[PDB]
Image 1 (tube, each protein chain N blue to C red):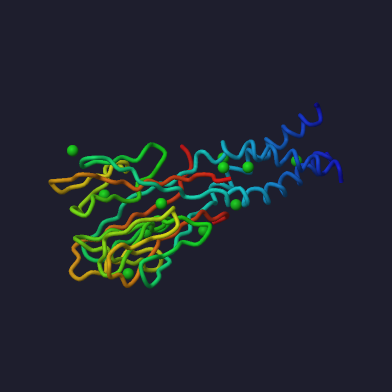
Image 2: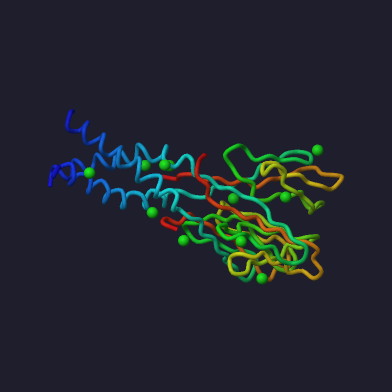
Length: 89
Length: 89
Length: 89
Ligand SMILES: [Cl-]
Ligand SMILES: [Cl-]
Ligand SMILES: [Cl-]
Ligand SMILES: [Cl-]
Ligand SMILES: [Cl-]
Ligand SMILES: [Cl-]
Ligand SMILES: [Cl-]
Ligand SMILES: [Cl-]
Ligand SMILES: [Cl-]
Ligand SMILES: [Cl-]
Ligand SMILES: [Cl-]
C-alpha cells in the first residue's frame, strides 16, 4: 500500500512533534466541593483526592472515587477535594 | 469526500494506536510542605491535593487553591500535599 | 507539494480534535493499600496522597514518597492512599 504507507509515515512524523508539545501543556485542576451533612460529591469528570469533615471528625471514607462520606454521628459538613486533568493548561 | 474520509480514518487509527505510548511518560509527582502553625502553602506550579493537621484535627480548608488551613484551636503544625504533572526523563 | 501540504493540514486539524477528546478519557485513579503493622507502600508508577493508621493512631509520615509509616507504638494496620493517571475508555 505505497500511498497508505507514505501517508502513514507522514502522520507518524507529525504526531512525533504534536504529542510532546500538547502533553507538556496538560495541567491539573483541583477544587473543593463542600456540603452540609455527611456526604460531599465530586463532579462527573473528576476524582476524589481527599476529604475533610467538620466538628474535627477524623473518620471518613471515599465511595467509588466520587463521594466523601464523613462517618461521625454528629457531622455538620463534609468536603471533597476533586481533581481532573485540564488540556492546554 | 471519499479520499478525505479514508485519510481521516487513517489519522484516527494511527492516533488511537500511538496515543498510549505517547502519554506513558506523564505522571503525578507529589511532595509535602509542612509548617509550624495553622497554614502550609504549596509552591507556584503545583496543586493542593490534600491537607493534614497536627494533633487530632480532621477539619481543614484550602485558601485560594494554594494554602492548607487547619481549623481546630491550637494546632501545632500543618502539612499540604502538593502535586504536579511531570513528563519523562 | 500541494497534496503533502493538504494532508499535513488535515493531520494537524484532526490532531486538535482528537487530542482533547483523548485526554477526557484519562482520570486520576486512586486506591488504598492496607498492610498489617506500621508500613504500607504504594506501588511503582503511583504517588502517595496520604496515610491512615486506624482509630487508634493519627501520627504518620511518608518515606521516600512511597511508604506510609504510622508512628504510634501499637499499630494493627497501616493504609496508604495511592494515585496514578489511568485511561478509561
Ligand atoms: Cl497545547
Ligand atoms: Cl474509592
Ligand atoms: Cl503561563
Ligand atoms: Cl509524547
Ligand atoms: Cl512559590
Ligand atoms: Cl493564607
Ligand atoms: Cl508539510
Ligand atoms: Cl522501621
Ligand atoms: Cl511526610
Ligand atoms: Cl480504556
Ligand atoms: Cl475504545
